[PDB]
Length: 158
Length: 158
Ligand SMILES: O=c1nc[nH]c(=O)[nH]1
Ligand SMILES: O=c1nc[nH]c(=O)[nH]1
Ligand SMILES: [Zn+2]
Ligand SMILES: [Zn+2]
Image 1 (cartoon, rainbow over the protein chains, first blue to last red):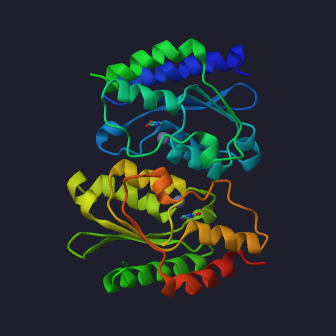
Image 2: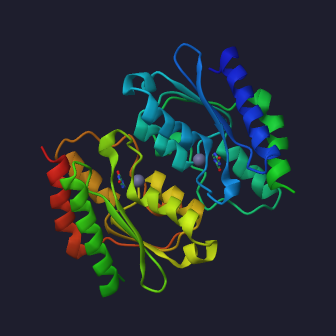
């Protein structure tokens, strides 16, 4: 399901999540990749300037809306370190992007938060296909479960 | 309870939706109201230029994160002609806005779209509280339902 190439991109997402963490933001990174394997756009979380909606997948949906034809959007892939929240999953579906691949699920992150005693997000951790039934979704990647546990702990578990 | 003040704001939302319809956009309008009864920001749907995520409730959330302190956001009210889609409900809860009042439910709109044989949105019509469990939500308003049915019919009927 997750190819070797798919892993390479998820690892790039983990590196963008790390840049975010190192810069004071939350550890989420995301990459948009055309059908050919060329990276079109990369972004990471930027909520530290006060806007909690500054999620990378959202910015990818809007970048694609402005710069890609619908046909090209349907055949592009979004890679993300963490599974799209409902905001990001709906935006993705609204603009007509294609396959999503995630390293860790929002269910896992949900679970990990409570284990540390951290406050739950005000947004439910709904799987992507509850929000967006038509989207092709792959993940998680078992290889990245430990790394993402560590990253998420660095930010949310003290 | 939807009060008489609330209904006045919903009627302004219906007017903004009609402005969207006359401009060639989809009929959605929303208003952000301070706890003092002051209108702070007003917007409507702007998707015709090709960005399908140009929902007014989402513009409200970003304007609020930019312009209001967290505490002022929590005490302000968002009025909307149509119930927040999952993208907009999530954004609202991320930035920590308060009460939502809507004139017509996304369930009502979904049923109407099915009657017209209109193609269903790529985003599921989840109730606000499925996405954002902590938000106080009121509506629909029985008195504006037929009015919004007519505006929807103008855009989506066939
Ligand atoms: O930047 C983000 N991307 C997905 N979910 C979340 O809470 N934050
Ligand atoms: O502008 C919008 N607001 C709510 N739902 C929708 O499809 N569009
Ligand atoms: Zn998100
Ligand atoms: Zn919306």
